[PDB]
Every structure is written in C-alpha cells, then in structure tokens.
Image (cartoon, coloured by chain):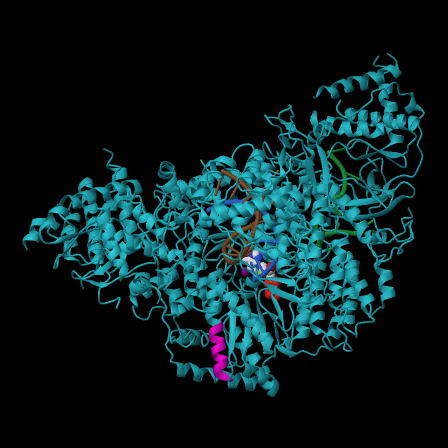
Chain colours: A cyan, B green, C brown, D blue
Amino acid sequence: MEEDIAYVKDLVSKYLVDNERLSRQKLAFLVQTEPRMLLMEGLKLLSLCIEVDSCNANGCEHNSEDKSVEKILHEVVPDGYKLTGNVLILLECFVRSSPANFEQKYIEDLKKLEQLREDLKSVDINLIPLIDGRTSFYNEQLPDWVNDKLRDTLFSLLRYAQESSRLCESLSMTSGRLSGIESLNTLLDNRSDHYEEIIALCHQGINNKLTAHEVKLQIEEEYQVFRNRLRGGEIKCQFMRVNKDHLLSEFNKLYIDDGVVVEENLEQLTHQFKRASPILRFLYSDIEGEHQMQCWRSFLNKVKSLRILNTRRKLLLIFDTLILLASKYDHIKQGCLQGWLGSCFVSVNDRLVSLDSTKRDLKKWIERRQQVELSKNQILSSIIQKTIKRATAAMFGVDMSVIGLDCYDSIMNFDVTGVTPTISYQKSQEETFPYAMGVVELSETTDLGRLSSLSLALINSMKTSSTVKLRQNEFGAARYQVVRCKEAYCQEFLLDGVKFQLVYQKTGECSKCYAINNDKVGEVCSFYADPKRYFPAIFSAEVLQATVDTMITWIKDCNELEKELTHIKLLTKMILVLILAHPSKRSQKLLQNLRYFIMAYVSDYHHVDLMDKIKEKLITETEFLLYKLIRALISLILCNEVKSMMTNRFKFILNVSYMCHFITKETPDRLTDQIKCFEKFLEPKIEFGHVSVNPADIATEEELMDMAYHAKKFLSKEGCTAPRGPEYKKPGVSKKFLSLLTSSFNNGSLFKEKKELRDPIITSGCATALDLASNKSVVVNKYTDGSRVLNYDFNKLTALAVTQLTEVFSRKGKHLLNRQDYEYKVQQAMSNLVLGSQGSASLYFDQLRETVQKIVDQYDTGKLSDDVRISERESNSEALSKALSLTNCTTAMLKNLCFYSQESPQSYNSVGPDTGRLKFSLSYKEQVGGNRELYIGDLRTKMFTRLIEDYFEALSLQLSGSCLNNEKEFENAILSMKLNVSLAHVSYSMDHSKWGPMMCPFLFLAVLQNLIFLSKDLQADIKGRDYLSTLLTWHMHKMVEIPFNVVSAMMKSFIKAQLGLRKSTSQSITEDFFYSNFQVGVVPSHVSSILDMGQGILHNTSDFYALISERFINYAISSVCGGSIDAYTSSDDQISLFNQDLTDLMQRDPEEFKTLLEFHYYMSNQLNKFISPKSVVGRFVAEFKSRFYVWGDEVPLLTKFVAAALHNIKCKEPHQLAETIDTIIDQSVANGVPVHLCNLIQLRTLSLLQYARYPIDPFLLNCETDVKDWVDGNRSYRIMRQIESLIPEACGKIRSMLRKLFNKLKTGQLHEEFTTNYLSGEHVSSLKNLCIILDVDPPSESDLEFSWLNLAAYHPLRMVLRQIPTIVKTIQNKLSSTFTRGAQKLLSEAINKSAFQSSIASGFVGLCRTLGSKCVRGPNKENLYIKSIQSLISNTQGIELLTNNHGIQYWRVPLNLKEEKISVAGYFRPLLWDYMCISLSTAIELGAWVLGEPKAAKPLEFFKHNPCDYFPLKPTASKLLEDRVGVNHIIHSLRRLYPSMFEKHILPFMSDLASTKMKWSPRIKFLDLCVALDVNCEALSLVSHIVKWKREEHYIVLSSELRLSHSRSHESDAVDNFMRQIYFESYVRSFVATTRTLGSFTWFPHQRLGPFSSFVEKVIYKGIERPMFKYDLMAIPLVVHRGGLWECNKRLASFSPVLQDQDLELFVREVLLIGALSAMMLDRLK
RNA sequence: GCGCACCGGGGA
RNA sequence: AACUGAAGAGUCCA
RNA sequence: GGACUCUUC
Ligand SMILES: Cc1ncnc2c1c(I)cn2[C@@H]1O[C@H](COP(=O)(O)OP(=O)(O)OP(=O)(O)O)[C@@H](O)[C@@H]1F
C-alpha cells in the first residue's frame, strides 16, 4: 500500500515522455497522497497520454488548454482539431474495455458531434467527425513494462483501500503487448559479485570486433597448421574412405570374439532356426491333426462376477463340483469328451482344476458333516441347492437344466484317466519335444498362423482375474522345476483341429512361465513370456506375408540375383518370424543399426568408429541367430558380383532394418531403463568434473566458486596449436573460434544477402496460459516449515531399503539359499529388526541397527515410503488452474503468471528468483531402440524456459536455414536435397552426438553476451541482452532431481555390498558416486552442473546456436578452399549440400577433400558440436529427418508404416479404434505403402473388432479402397463409397437428387423447402418430398427400409472403469480462450474429462472387457448387453440381416415397427438418409465432384506391374481461395441472423474488431443457410465443413495402382471486402484516412492495391500510425468523401471496386437515400 | 527359454 | 503409486 | 478451442 504508491510515484517520475502537456499532470500526480486523489490523478494522466498519441496518430492538434468550439472558431470541448480551408476535423477519444459499453460511449460521441454538424456545416465550413475509441489503457508514451506495473498498482489501490466504482475496469484489462521478459524490472535486482564474475568470464580473451580481413587471415592460418599436423600424423583422422568390400567383411566378423561361428549355409541356418526356442520349435513342428458343461460354466462366471468378491475355498469348490456334475451328465447322455485335459477340467475362472484332488478334497469336506449332523447323499444336494437359490437371486436367461444335480454318488465312482499337465520352469532339451520338429515349410503361411493363435492366447491370459488358489502344486525346491498342475489357469486355442491349452499360474500383465499342453501328449513346450509384447502377430497372418512379398517384388528384376531370390525370401521371412516370436529390445537395436550400415555402404566417406557404433550387445541365442540371418541376407544381396539395380537393393535392406518397428516401444523392464537413463545423465558430468551434490536454494559459497571454476574450464579448449593438438571427446568451446564466430556475426559476414536484424524483445511471441496446458506431467514441490524440501533423509531411506530387502528375502531367500550359511544368518538378523510390518560388517550392522531403531521409534511402511519422497506430480492443467486462481487480471498470459500473480517472486539473484531455483526432475522415455532421459520441470521452470524459447525462436525465424519452426524452409530443404541427389553432387548427411548432454546454458550465455543484434540503437540492445543473460543464468544453476526409484535401488545395493552379499566387486562409475555419498552419510538428492542444457528443454535456443555456428563453419570452409556448402539444420540434425566445385574436388584430389572434411570436423568440435559416427558423405543418397532421397526412384518405408498399424493402440471404443486405423493408413498410403496391403490391414482391424463381439456396421472401415479414396477423398468419402457398394441402386437416385439440389442451394434458390421443411422431422417423408420437388424419381419403398444398427443411439457406450448450439460454443471457446475466467472454464472441463478418460480400460483387452459388459444404454435409463439387443432383434419379425463378403452388416427394417411397439426400432437408422447427410456434408467440404457418377476403370492396357514405379501425386481440388470462409464470416452472419444470442454469448468475448461492421458485410448465401441449420439442428454441422479443406500434401503412390482406381467427376474476396466497405461508407459519413480509421474496418488484410498501395503495403504493416497524405499515393490528412479521396475541396484521387448486382443490394439495404444514389451514379462514370 | 543396471519377475 | 519439450498431419468432441 | 492417436527431432 504505502510502499507501492511511492514506487509508482518514482516509476512515473523516472519513466515518462518529456511532453509539456503531460508534465502538468505529472506534477499533480506526485503530490496527491490521498489514495482516491492519487487514483484519480493517475487515471487522468493515463487518459492524457493515451489521447496525446492518438492526436499524433490522426494528425489532429491537441487541445492542451481545453479550447472550446468557440475558441478555435474565433481563431462541446473537442480533443483535437485540424481546421484548415473548408475542412474541419474534430477528434475525441475514450478508453472503454467492455464491447457493450464501447457502443454506448461511441453513440454518445456521435450524438455530441451530430448535434452541431448541421449548425457548423450550415454557413461555411463542413464538419468531418472522427472517433478514436480505444479498448485498453495501452499508453505507449510510457515504456511497455511500466504500463503493466502502473496498471497493477492503480487497480490494487481501489481494490484494497477504496472499499467505499466498478465502472472503468480497464484497470484489470491487461495493457501489455510484448513477450513479458521486460517485466523483470518489476522485481528487485540483487545480482551480486557472482554475476559480474560470470559475465567477465564471458567477456575475456574474446575479441568480437574483428574485421572480415582479420577473421579470414586467422582462419587460413588454422588451416595450414591443421593440414600440416594432419599429414604429419599428429592429428587423428576421423573419416575413412568407403570400400564396400572391406565394409561387408567387417559386418561378417562383427561378433567373432563372442563365439559366433565363422559362417554357415542356408541348410544349417534353417535347421537352427526351426528349433531355436520353444515357440519356434512349436511353430514348425508336426501337430499331426449343446453341452450342459458349458451351460453351468458360462453361467457361473457371471454369478461370481455379480455377487460378493473374495470367494472362499468352500464357494469355489461347489462350482467345481457342479461343473463335474454337468460333465458327467453330458458324458452319460450325449457321449462327449471335450472340456478336459487329461484328468483336469476347465472350471469357472479358467481354472484347470484336477479331478483326483477335487475328489480327495470332497472326501474330507463331507466327512466333516458326519460329526456335524439328512445323510451324506442328501446333505451335499442341500449345499448345492442353497447355492443354486442364492445364485439365481441376482436378477435363468441362458438355458440351464437343474436335473443334473440329483445326488453325488457319481463322483464316488467317476474316473477319468489321461496325461497330467505340467510346466517346466527350467530349460528342457529339444528331445523331450514330442512332435517331429522342423516339418512345416516356410514357403507357406502355416507358421504365421500358429503364431497368430498362440499370440492371441498370450494376450487373453491378461484378462483372467486373480482368485484364491487353494491346493498348492509343489512344496519347497520343486516349485520351479517340472510342476504337476493340480490347479492352474488355462487358455484354450485350436490349431488345425487340435485343441491346445496355454497353461499358466500367475494372473496379470507380468512376465510368467507358460506351458502349452495337449490332451494326447501332456506338455508340449514351456517358455517365459511377457504377454504385452505379443500383440502385432494377432490376425496378421496375411498382412505379414504380403509385406514380405511386396519387398521381394522390388528385387525380382536383378538378373544377377535371379538364382538367389528363393533364399532371400526365406531369410526375410525368417527374420520377421523371429522378431515376432521373440520381441527383444536388443534385437530391435540390432535391426535398427542396419540402416547406418547400409547408409555407409552406398556412400563415399564414413566415420572411422562406425562399426563400433553398429555393434550391439547381444545376450540370448535367438539374438545371435538373428544376427546370423541378417549377415546371410546382406551377404546375398550386397555381393560384389551383383552390380545393377542398386537403388532397389538399398530400398530392400533399409526396409529390412525398419522391421525393428514390429517390436513394441514399451519398456521390457522399468527399473533397469530408469537406472540406465540416470547413468546417461550422470556419466558426462563425472567425466568433466562438475557434479554439485545437494544444492540449496540459497547457494553456498563453495558451489558458486565451483561453478565459476568450471565455467572458466569450459572455455579453455585447445586446438591444433597446442603441443597435444586438438582434443576431441572433451566438452568445451575454444576462445579463438568463439571470438571468430561472434566476430563475423557482428560483422555481417555470416548472414548476408548487409543485413538488418530487428529487436527480438518486440518481435517475440506472446504466450497465453493455455499454450502451456495439457494433460502431461509437471513436478509439484513439497514444503515443510515453509521451506521447500530438497534432500532425501538418510535415516528414512536406509530404513525403507532395509524393509524392501526383508520383503524380497521373505519371498525368495527364506525358502532357498542354504539356510545354514552366511547370507541366511546375515539377512535373518537384518530382517528381525524390522518391526511393524507383517570385519566391517559388524560395525555396519551396528550402525544399521541404530538407524532402524531410530526410525521405528519415530513411526509403518506406507507413511515411511510417502515421507521419503520429496516431490509430487500433477498435470499441466491442474497446476495452471491452481495458478490462475491467484492472478488478478483478465487476459491469461504467461507474464501475468510469473510476475504479476499473487505467489510471484519479489526479488531475484543470478542463481534463481525469490521462490527457489529452477528445478527439473528425471524420467525415461519409451521409444524404439534406446534410452531418452526426460526433464520435467515444475510450473515456474516451465514458464520461465518458455519465455526463453519464445525469444530465441523469434531470433531464429529472422535468419534463413533452420527447419525447426519453419515449414517453408523444410520444404525448400527437401527440394534442395532432391535437386542435389539428382545432379549427383556430394551431400553430407550429418548428425550430432550428445546435443543436450554437452551444450550448456553457459555456452549460450557467452555467445549471447558477445553478439550484437541491433547495431543502430545500442542501449535497448544491451538491455534486452541483459534480460536474457539473467534468464539464462537461472538455467546455469538449475537443480535436476534424482528419481526416487534410482536412489532406493542404490541404497539397497549399498547395504548388500556392505554386508558382503554380492558375487563380484565390480562397480560402475554411478555406483561409486552413490556409494561415496552413502558412506559419509549424505543422500544425493539434486545435482547441479555446468553442462546439460536438458533434452529438448532449450530446443529453440540450441537450434539458434546450431544455425549461427554452422553458418560460420560453412563460411570458413568456403574461404579456405573454393566451393560452397548449403546447410539446413534442425537442432541436432543437419544436411550439408555440397557445391559442384567441391564435388569435382572430390575426384580431382581426394586427399584435399579428406583434409577439408577433417577440417570441418575440427572446426565443429572446437565449437562444441560432436559429429556422430553415423554420419556419411556421399553422392548416392541424402538424409534429413528420416527422409531418404536416392536419385531415380522413391524410398518408401513400407515396414515402418505397416508395423505402426499392427500395435496395441490405446483406444477405448470401437469407433475410435476404426478412426485411428483409418488415420494411420492414410499416412501409410501417403508414404509409399501399396493399397492392397492397406485393405489387408483394415480387414485385420475388422477381425479384431469381430473377435471382441461387436456388430460391424457400415460406418467403421472401408476395406475395398482405391488410390483415389485416399489421395482425393477424406474419411467421409470412404464411408460414402462403402454405402454406395452396399446399396448401389438407391444411392444413384439419392445422388441424382443431390446433384440437382446442391446446385440450387449454392445459387440460393430452394432454401425454405430445404431448411425449415425437409431437414427436420420424419426422415423418409423428407427424402421423398425432396426428390419430388426437384423432379427426380423418389427412392422406391423397398429402398427406404435399409438401415443400420446404431448401438449408441440413445446414449454412448458405457465403458468399464479400471480406476446452446455447437456453433456458438465453437466461436465462444475460440474467442474466450484468452481470458482468465474463460481459460479457467476450459481448464476445468479438460481436467474433469481427462480424469474420466484415465479410468477407462484401454487397449484390446479393455475393449473386449467393455464389449462383454452391459455397455448398451437402453432407451430410458437402463443398460443391456449387446447380446440382449441382438436377441430382441432376432425375435422381432421382418427385420432381416444382410452382409457383404467382408462382414459388413446392414439390416432391413419394415416401415411399420416403430408404430407397432418395437423397443428395438429406436436403435436402427435409415441408411439412405445417412448417406444423403454424409454425401452433402462431404460435398460441401471436398467439392462438387463427390456427387458425380462412380465409374470403374477399364484400363485393359496389359501393362507391367513395375513395383517401384512410384509417382508423387497431389490431391486435386477446385476451391482454394473462393471458399476460404473464416471465423469472421461466421461471426458476422451469426450477428445478422441471431442478434440476441450473439450479444449474449459472443459479444463480451470479442475484441480486435470491437463491432465495426458498419452493415456492409457481403451477406453470403449458402453460409446463412448453414448457420441457420446449425443453430436449429445439432445432429450435423455443415459450417464446420465449410471452414475445412483437404490439404495439398503429396502422396507417393504406385503408378500401377493409380490406374485401377475409380473415376468420379461432376462439375480474393478478403481484399475486396475491405474495398467494399470504404466505397460505401464514404457516402453516409465522410471519414479521415488514417492508420486507425482504415484498420478499424473489420475486413482488412493481416502493387495491385492501387489507391492505398503505399500505406497498407509497408506503412500500415510496419506499425507507424500516421495519416495518409497526398504526398504518398501518387501534412494535410485526406478526408475520404463520397466516391473519392479529397485534399482541399477536390478529388485528387479516386477509388472504386467492381460493383455487382448483389453488391448494390447491401447499399440499398441500409435501413437522403436518393441523394446518395445520385452522387453514386455520377462517380461510376469515371 | 522372461528381464539381463550382478539386484527384478516367475502359485494366496 | 512413473513417461518431458517441440514439429507435421489426421480424427473426434462441444 | 479442447482431447486423442500416428510419424519425426
Ligand atoms: C526432447 C526429446 N524427447 C524425446 N525424444 C527425443 C527428444 C529429442 I531433442 C530427440 N528425441 C528422439 O530420440 C531418438 C534418437 O535418439 P539417438 O539416436 O540420438 O540416441 P543417441 O544415444 O543420442 O545416439 P548418438 O549420440 O550417437 O547420436 C529419436 O527418436 C529422437 F531424436
């Protein structure tokens, strides 16, 4: 309060323009100490400074002395004047924020001027009214951040002290326009000696003012020394000429010292393959191939799923006895033997329960009732009878005869004999296998079909719900050997008429032991598996064969591979079946590196360490088998005898390497992945030297000295002039090369076209709150005693690790491990001391006892484990919605949350703001072949780093060469790569190792401190560079948190190693780091270091550095040796397109070219950029962002996009799954995959849906598509094209009617007979009437009966839980997202929706669960199984079912059932009506060709297939600029048609236009129709299709499949809308031509301009708000009078649009009308 | 026969 | 009681 | 405008 008022008195005094007019108000604002008087003076001063630039904007002279109208006339009270000649310009200004109130004030001003217009214009001088109403207190007389600081204080005065008014509330409307970095002045600057030290480091020995001559003389003396010491052997070469003969020999011998055999032929290789593993033994072996039992079983599963849980031992056994009774009854009557496996039978919950023990258990149970008091034969029946009544109570249904429950004497003499089911937990030789292994051929699809059935049973094993497993199998040490299953779980599958059973014991998603079991032979095989990894092979037996056949067609023409095609096909199929049977991550990586191998092979130079990068650590036998198969395949295709068709073989092998995508992304183990990610984070820092363990918010002195020391060490890299020479592998940037890079940026040598940067504080993007909101994660700090917690507790962590070790001992070590030995005694002693829960070793155990006793005094496991954590997690939206509940502004921008919020920092240092330092946290990413460490900062960190990124993206977009935030630049890069490979020019396909882990914010700080952006004005330049220096130093001192699991695992490992409980004494660096700290007594919680920018955190910042540094490197090389380079970078990726002279030099003197490549390597490394070993130089192929470009062909990644669609996509309802697969397949077709393979993938998805027991309606997938259904259509077109094949006769009549209709609506003729007649009501009568009124034969009565079953008709499907128009809502949300209350409503809705969606079971297993439950909502508040609906349809008479070949179900429902009391007639929807609606909406979107006649192709040209005839194609379209209907059109139409609802819902949220339509909008026909329909009928939205259009991205399609596709064919206003308003407005009220008046008109662009070309093109666009003058346009403002531009009573210029028949309707529809008409006509002549 | 950071998972 | 920062595209929803 | 899914870095 009292301090804030003094602060703003100082701020206004210090910062304010020296204008005398404002001075009088400034001297009065500094003295009114009364808070009300201070507030009034402040508002007055803001109003004066707003009205003083508007007068300087519109040219009017300011009435400083409030000269009344009489005063100026002699020489009510205006705010301006320009009276000259007969032209008087009266200006008045105001500031209102409410768009409703704005109108009131504007009307008042109009009245105040119009009450004297007549009197003034009566005698001599004519009046020209002018208004400059503003919507906020912007006031650029004050500097930008002050307008926010002053506004906040001014508002707070009345909000806190003036409690005695809510009218001028623009004091809440935020008045800023910039990024928000400048708001750091609102905080106190406490930057002490440390900041000065860091900056002095950044500015020491670095001479950034070199001229181009000094730079070019210093850069050609690095080259002489480098070249001489490279020829002399003192510098290690890093690039090797490609041999193609010594490079294959290197892949063959890659694993020679791991024991792999020298070589093998196919016969031994196939023999090994068909026997390697239990699955692979089983896939190629020789398998050599109603009932009351199911009625009880299928009925008792429901009974326990609808009754009490925790079914006791007694209750489950009754179900076993009942199933046995049913089985005996079926045996006696029917004479059948199914449902058994030897002497075990399938009981209720998959349970493979055994007869002998089920009989034996019943012997004891009945014997109990002998002493418990009719007889045994009657007592057991009464047990079942009591259960039977209770089971039936929960309301049979399915048939279930009760007569099979008479007595139990049958059990007493029931004997079933057979084999026993077993699981072998230990490895068994391939001699116990009972089938002739290796018989099934590979040339067919028998093996891919057995994997499909077996994989499906591995996925189904995750659905079993865990229940009590009485009757254990084995005891002691036999439990992990051959186990005789007395009670397990089983899943039955059926292979070629043989009933196999997958037998397991553990229920869940974890890795288990499975055993395949047969009724004739007992166990078949056993294995260990993680079921979640086995989904892609399900129902894909035909996709995975067409994939291999497609790849083989590529190489079928190589005449010198003509005798080797059979082996190549065999080997490819072997590779595919191996990676599908054994989904290993170490095989994923091995298949992935093959793309780098082949990329090197086709290229010219490669890194010397390439083959150390390709090598992968293999473990199992199948991984070495996979390497053997890959070696054989490559050795076949890449022979030196084969020379022709190299492009096809590169394509082939690259797709073989992309087969790695058939293995799931998910982590095989989480803890290992997390430990490895942390090792990746920590190892580079330990190797550098800087790991500051456990930093604090108030950084100590030792930490600061360490950071300064290592910052100094970062910059001291040496190169090629030191005796040791350049030292790669060392992080750092030189000083010579830093002061050359900045010396030539500050010189206009890098970016020349001579350049003109512009200040990136002004041009930086402004980020709202919702830009940073999502459902992703964010760290939440934990506070105790009011201070953030940053340290794990050693006592609590030690106790927790001891408890975990005790648990693991109890499960595993207690029952094994030679219980009289050392380790048993040690871990027993360590386990007794844990209470509550259900040598140096002596000293350490003493300490451990003390610590655990201390903790158990303090507390017993859940609380401890939650008290060790130091962080929590939320979503971005939860944190933001909590944050916006603290701010006090209207607009929700980031600057309002960091600096002007309630919990915002107050002072700041160079280490961090008042509210702690920036803090991240670590997690891991699940990706294909590799570990990514992920940094999740808390909310404040995310906001501040977002400000940094906005700044550096603003810089990067001003310089040409970065493809990170520039799609035009990326397309130019693609075109340049294509042209380069076309001419056979060299092209270096670069890649950078350790982008994140090596570049640091200190490097960016040094570079920023030495760069000069605006060399015209230096003060603002240095000030902005200062703001960014501060923000980048906050990232120098960030604290990265060590995950909880990592420290917990490390402490368990520590305790084990301390007690001696470990085999070896090998320790990686990370374990040393953790153990050194655990010994002294401190837990490493957070880590600070000089390195590690963060993976993708400073992404735009590092992209900017990459851009400028690469530009310097290419410039240096061009200066050194001729030529040139064209580099496109994308922040860790680069493509360098060499010149033609460099390409020639490669052939002239290849030693010189290798010297130039080595010099490029050296210069890059001296600037902290380590080129990856996966970097090639070549003339054959290019590479940028996984997009390969060979010369005379296209490279489709067929296997990546086939494999994308086959995975367990996390989808929740059966229509979402179909839409997802449609999208993936659209992507595939766009990227080279043929279409006949896409149809197979769609059939695979439909089969997955059918397995789930879902009715397959015509609206799921179209599995008969062409090329044209993807290139030219969208999803709605594919739905049309499926319905047009189900009922092709009627759709012809519907399309004839639609062609006749759509043509009339667009013209605008038949609107009422469509709108409010026959798009509402009974659908069939509507369709008939529409056909009648257009003179088209109506659909026959039979055609109107076709229907489709809509199971979500009444309400969407109720999915199991694991745990106002739409047009107005659309525009409302779009306009309201930028307001605090609007953002809060959106955020709250998203939070609740996400909390609901997270509890829904997702995936194939969840889909089957959902569709097996009561998922169909009945008409009036009830739930029914899908089977209930299908049964009621089956009973009802007349409803037929029809199906096409694929399985698409369309019904036939007579048109009298809805009347005739049919409860299942409300689920059906007529199919022609839906066809009409789909066809109409997609004709609005795609075009009018959709309504033409489908004509099949009659090619008959007898051409060759040519499988690699790929052809780029573009979706042909007709409307590009004609139908660019935007949001403004819909807003204007909505206001015109529905005013009250518009002003109730859309007016408050509307700005940047402020309702300045002036009633000259075009009044679009066919848009008002759509708007009127969407307000009324909310079933179909036509307006969302008008604003939608098919993109013009290219599709790479086979040129043969393009010929077989069907053929169908039927058939600037943005600028002119601006010109339209000016020409018609001028007549009613002549207006002044200024920047604010012209831009005020709603229609306005954001030398064909003609009359206003000069001002709009540059003057308006640049930002100078000046009046348009006669000096331009070929100091007196030009008043726009009726029909021409006027200067002094004469039309010095004239403007006129092309008036039309409809344009004149607006002008004559405006309510002096004749006078306006008369003057209009005279102008039209000239 | 899984995981394969020595450490976990593999019958309530 | 675990999985980020961006880029492109598509689908759905109100 | 929000959500979701694929590919990329
Ligand atoms: C911020 C972020 N969040 C999640 N994912 C990210 C990133 C970033 I920046 C890159 N990626 C992805 O990581 C894969 C390549 O990883 P990459 O092949 O480079 O492994 P690597 O160990 O660094 O190999 P080199 O150092 O020898 O180049 C690839 O999907 C993509 F690049």
Is A1117 colored magenta in this rendering? yes
Quarter of the figure with residue A640 = bottom right
- The spot of residue A1674 in percent (x, y) is 25, 68
- Magenta span: predominant SS is helix
> Where does the C terminus of chain A fall, quadrant-wise?
bottom left
Q: Is A1443 displayed left or right of A1336 in the figure?
A: right
Which of the pair A1073/A182 is nearer the observer? Answer: A182
- The spot of residue A1286 in percent (x, y) is 68, 44
Quarter of the figure with residue A1339 = top right
> Where does the N terminus of chain A fall, quadrant-wise?
top left
Quarter of the figure with residue A816 = top right
Query: Is A1410 rendered above or below residue A1136?
Result: above
Question: Which stretch did the figure color magenta?
Answer: A1110-1121
Which of the pair A583/A1072 is nearer the observer? Answer: A583
Q: Is residue A1012 visible?
A: yes
Quadrant field for ligand 1: bottom right
Which of the pair A312/A913 is nearer the observer? Answer: A312
Q: Is residue A1255 visible?
A: no
- The spot of residue A675 in percent (x, y) is 62, 54
Is A470 colored magenta in this rendering? no
| Residue at far front of view | A1335
| Residue at far left of view | A74
- The tally of labels here is 0
Q: Is A101 displayed left or right of A1419 in the figure?
A: left
Which of the pair A399/A411 is nearer the observer? Answer: A399
- The spot of residue A646 in percent (x, y) is 71, 74
